[PDB]
Length: 16
Image (cartoon, rainbow, N blue to C red; front, side):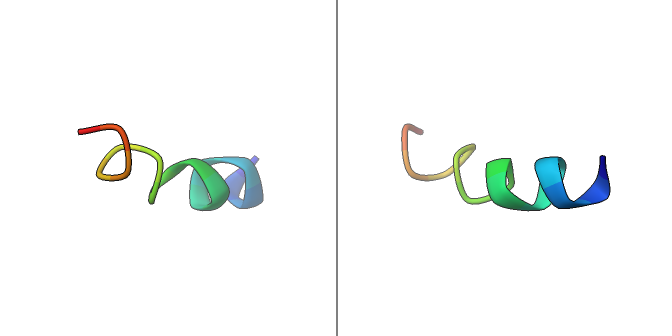
């Protein structure tokens, strides 16, 4: 669950 939010942490800035 911490690994899933780590992969998605650079997919807040990469779209936005």
